[PDB]
Image (tube, rainbow, N blue to C red):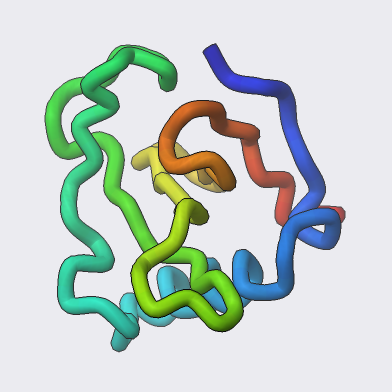
Length: 96
């Protein structure tokens, strides 16, 4: 299930950066950014394979990819933020 909605302005500034790269279709910091997200645990609504894609939300000072990501849904303005490594998700509202 989705944990409600959250304004983009209420997320880390890196979330905004990630959405800007997605808008320009890259380039991304990680060649894997953009890979299909399976939604294997069905946390997000059920959709066909390829409906979702995952992108890194950089964590300051991290040597790894961290636990922050943005999962895009193919629908317009459909984006999910996870700060706990795919455990929970919140719908991102870019209008606030």
